[PDB]
Image (cartoon, rainbow over all chains, first blue to last red):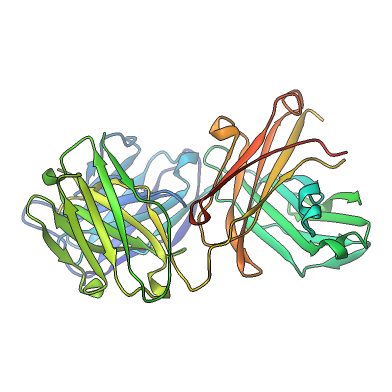
Length: 215
Length: 216
């Protein structure tokens, strides 16, 4: 089968820059007339979107910031200029030979200025407490870079058991990240303690952002 | 522009089979080649095979021979993918797609169908509204706890509230999936205007609405 090797596997690029992604085929994907290489953009949860077909043709409806080039085995996708909407994984695909095959993808991240998170804490809902459960939720929203540390403190003791952390994919508008940290306890365990704290440590400050409540 | 509309998410026991559909509107399926493409969680794309609906001719990646059967029905303008004797490695999102009107690119894609292969039964989510603790802007939340399998769809005010939303990818905890979402509005917007989290879970055929209400 034709193996398509993409490089880089991931890259970060700032707004307005030009960048290129490489796709190399294990054997030629060409006829006398065309290179049967196509490029797609995919964001998590959505289908792939066609950008470039037959190595160099711009798909209708796609911005003229995307261009493709190459022949034989060596292909290039160019993005110029890069915009915030371009945060996505990019795939090449060949159709010269069966089976059709895809490259393993290039994840494009947008580089921007550091931003501190906005932190919000949420006690268990009254409905969850009626059911006999208790989750404490903390949102750490619109920060950059993605690396961030969250710690839960219950009455002055740090706790990691039962914490579920989920990061959003990079925002297509402001290129920030957000994360949700949920501390799930039993209700009988929750109402035996009173002080609950979400602490966010991010490179935008040495002192953590602290949000807390008393049950 | 055209539209490819895929059938809904499915939970399948190991060893059973499932048949997915891809209904085309805006064009005649006889005038293109249809493809099915597999994407395992956090993985890349795998071409399964293709069909020419004008005569039914098929071509498969040998990897999927026996596992996958692609058909099409011109009477209903629909292409199908049957997956047989499912195992855990068949858990994936499956896409249909059409060729530019089989060696050109795939320019139109269905929205994907999530197939989960598991012996575990469906579990409906518990959906909890998250109001602020008992400024110029306020952040509200919705916790979607303990469902199986994926996916759920979450909206705010039936989708009319879409700016300022962060919906956090589902993850496994304690054997089930949990997902959450935040929405940030101006303090003159809430609680003055009602804000409701709407959660649909296809596998359990459930649809629940939770209004965010100030704590007391």
